[PDB]
Length: 346
Image 1 (cartoon, rainbow, N blue to C red):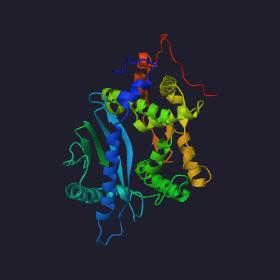
Image 2 (image 1 turned 135 degrees about the horizontal axis):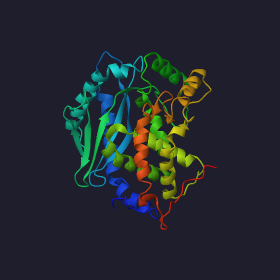
Image 3 (image 1 turned 30 degrees about the horizontal axis):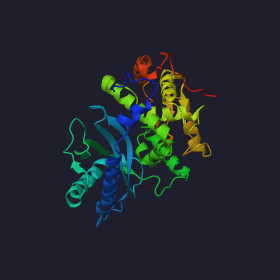
Image 4 (image 1 turned 180 degrees about the horizontal axis):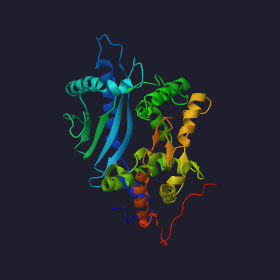
């Protein structure tokens, strides 16, 4: 149903129905990306003086956009380029890469056959330049629009289980410190962001998708004022990693634990040592710089410089106000009419 009234007794039955993505549509999209990824690497540039080439194409974060309930989703597709001198190059040469990618993307639409409907958008308005392509399957009425975000390849060839070279983060921090603008290069580390949320248990990933939709429902109210969606995703992971650590758990317990953290934002300092740590002196100091920043501070596991949900303390206040309202909703309330309760952090 609406889910404002969806009780806490079941919860999952709502996630399994409305929230769960189409299995058939995903498979079609994943294949379409593989066609494009394999297309861009070969086609882009080539027969060209400049050694810069497309190394890989990775899908980034995605958020279901409410229309009926879930009718559509917006995702980010990061195109990695090589032979760039610095991280800043992806910002300056962005317009140069936007044209080369768009040129072959249109050519890919003509030459390559797809199962879904490949849609290359017209030049985008209300934005400085912008680009995107839409993948839709009218049979299932599923639609997704990918925003192409060109980025330098920092990791090069990287596989899960391997901690990235600390030297890479050193170059990132030194360049982010001098030129300013902390956390703009997070797109290069997208592989680590996906790998962070991919290996999570099924019940947790379903919980995250529940939190994802909660964010979108409030996003059509307060607008862009609220913090980035990535903050809520990492916060859900933190709620599970602390005190629970169970394969099977209650969604009502977790959803309650996440909402109470939104109100605790001023008390929240969170960071992950997954892809980096204090072994390197340069990385260590920069990591301590972020921890002493005004709360809430959620440190991007893939981006030691990048602070998710930071820079605005009134963003979380607007979020905490609506988080307080949803606490009064039956969503968190069980059969008794009382609260299900949060997770013990012991």
